[PDB]
Length: 278
Length: 278
Image (cartoon, chains in turn red, purple):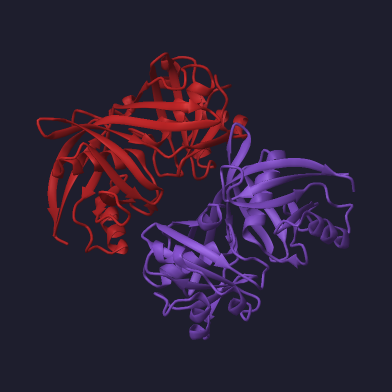
């Protein structure tokens, strides 16, 4: 048998944020079994907590219902939060396919309520499919350059001139299906406070609750394009239009050419707990 | 006249990794001239960028100081990185003697900092010269089976029980000279993180900085022998003992009998740029 929890990542209230199922003591499950269990659960990801192999605290494997992922932001945040229920340590070092990701855990009376991670440092380039993408979204132009970032998954960012315009978007999901192995992240805001909507037929999501792996890239994008500085944090509110509001905090330190840290943090809360029969 | 750059492949810092000289606009150079220029430069390889002949983006010819090679990992990575300075494309398709090798380029502010290639799928067998090889290396036994892989060059892998033992190796380079048309790759590590040293009198190298064409084979070797799974990436650190640390990332997808992809990736950095008078 295995124990699991369901953590709503990037939320402090259940039924908000982005759910992840976290399976404990998973060393007796072969990867094919892990994939089957992820399919059974049908959450956007399931994670599996394994003994470390390279000096970290645990090795985490991440599965969608149909494949294994090298990196994912919300699922790793939720795993850190879930695991921090079983450790007293302040920092947690989670081994993944992209290497060991360092988390800082934040508690109140022994319960982990939030965590902060150092993400992989992304790369980026111009999408070079602007007219096609804008058509698909139903708008004429972006504010800022349409660039695609890679940190495992790929995210494209399209800027809107107000939060109302972002909310008004009604993309052609069929036309967005021609954009393979990426997610389309639309954003609007000012100063410290930004809003985001993410759509990805490629990653099997109509509209996402919290795209944790896009938060870091978005901070970089906003700093490069002069809306914030390198080293300044932003608050990114996502998921409002699907009723899964999700709050991601991000900061990109250094400069574009030499980034030293990409920090993303958020709250998490337990939605449920249970046990499976295998 | 021709322009060239010197790229340190499998490094992000100059004077680390493995240098390659990359010559642009080489269509006016006959192959005998290319060989002379490679001899002049005396780098482990020089590459020459030619117009494509089969639908790729460019045709790349690869020369050591004394012969043409059908395939080489570090030199092709360095060429992709150098060329990506002159294209906006995300993917680069480089024609070679073994066929067209697909690269994904990774940029920051227009500069290509890293790339990933799909390598030829190797073949392998038992070396069947274990006592002789072990004698030459100065050790009694390998950890894992002593197997030789072929993907153009041939690499043999000998496993050591700790990184300290690997570092302590002092091979008899004269005794290694009886091993023709191959390189001897010694390795140690665990989990995601491995160390390698490569010696090859046959290929005219006392000790290599980054043996890019051995990284893929090593991932296969480790998966076949149960140290990693098929589909899991490894980080391979090579060259430390000669002060040319080199970081190669590799992953072998499928299974031993039906490999579907052998991915090898790394950083690269420009060491220098110049022009020749012919």
